[PDB]
Amino acid sequence: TSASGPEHEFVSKFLTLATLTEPKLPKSYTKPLKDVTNLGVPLPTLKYKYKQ
Amino acid sequence: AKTLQRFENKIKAGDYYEAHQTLRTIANRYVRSKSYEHAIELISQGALSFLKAKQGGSGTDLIFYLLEVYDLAEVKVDDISVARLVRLIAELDPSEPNLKDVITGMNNWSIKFSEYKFGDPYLHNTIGSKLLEGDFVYEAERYFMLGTHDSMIKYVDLLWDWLCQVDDIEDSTVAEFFSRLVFNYLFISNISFAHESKDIFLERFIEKFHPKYEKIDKNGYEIVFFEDYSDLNFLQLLLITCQTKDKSYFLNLKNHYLDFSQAYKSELEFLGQEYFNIVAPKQTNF
Ligand code: PRO
């Protein structure tokens, strides 16, 4: 419905602009794990305790 | 073959010190005369039956002995090398007090004797699973992240099961889990895993929570547009943006979602560096 029209329009337009030509890296792109030098930035801890 | 029997006799009898001591002095003799394959088979088999017999201390000691010989004999990381370690990891009690030491030992050998900075991926797949059995969730995550395609499956399951355990779910709750797949796979530049795990995860989310959504498709790319999960839209767009390596799209995206830009400040600064060569630091919006 039209309560989220603004964000729908924005997402749709952004997707069109982003895919006017084939993106530099294809979906199937994988950096060989041999070449991975670092692991980026630490992600936050989750609030939730973990069980099973 | 013959002293393997004398050994597993001493193990059925519960003579653990004799079994251990005898095997070690016999293993020493093989190492001494440079018969490394013999020492490797004896030591690993020995480790296995201590672990099967719930003798963590002696089996663990023999795993370290194996790794010492692996290092001595300059045993390269290959399928046979790794399978010996995988077979052993299987029999390790998740509770073993030195589990993490053993894991680090194995991984460190795989770093030294391969071209992986962080260790063999196939080995990581098994280590990951063990760690998860011990509820070492954050360690499992890392090893899966650095694992194989199977690891990616296991990782999604890890995250999905965890989200389902959460008693009071929320709009920001789903993103806390989903963002982890997008970020981690973007960090190691596995776009393929990023896409594939996003698809598994979002499908399961749709089938369980029945959110309001519509699939937007343009030139073979798809965003699942959620009416009530802005975070989820942003995260999907982020992945495609990184693929384009276009700074202006990256900027546009951030300018539209000011809050998410603040929430993912350090992640986004790194992605800006990795995918867009942005040298300028993040100017803090607040
Ligand atoms: O370790 C080696 O290389 C030899 C071959 C079988 C066992 N001893």
Image: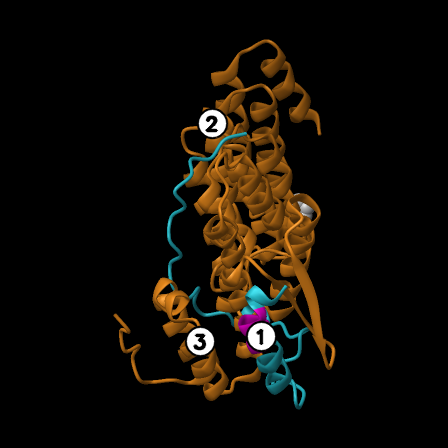
The residue carrying mark 2 is B95
Tag 2, which chain? Answer: B
Q: Residue at x 41, y 78 (%)?
A: B255
Residue A11 tag number: 1
Q: Position of residue B275 (x, y in %)?
A: 48, 80
In the image, is residue B276 above or below residue B133? Answer: below
Q: Position of residue B4 (x, y in %)?
A: 66, 26
Classify 10 Å Cα crowding around label 1: few (below 14), some (14-19), many (20 and above).
some
Identify the residue position indicated by label 3 in the image.
B256
Under mark 2, the amino acid is Ser
* The hue in which chain A appears in the rendered picture of the protein: cyan
The image quadrant where one finds the N terminus of chain B is top right
Image location of residue A5, percent across then percent down: 58, 71
Q: Which mark sits nearer the N-terminus, 3 or 2?
A: 2
Question: How many circles with numbers are drawn on the protein?
Answer: 3
Q: CA distance from mark 1 to mark 3?
A: 10 Å
| In the image, residue B278 lies in the stretch drawn in magenta | no
Name the spot of residue B157 as percent of width and height, x first.
62, 45
Above or below, comparing residue A24 to residue B68 in the picture: below
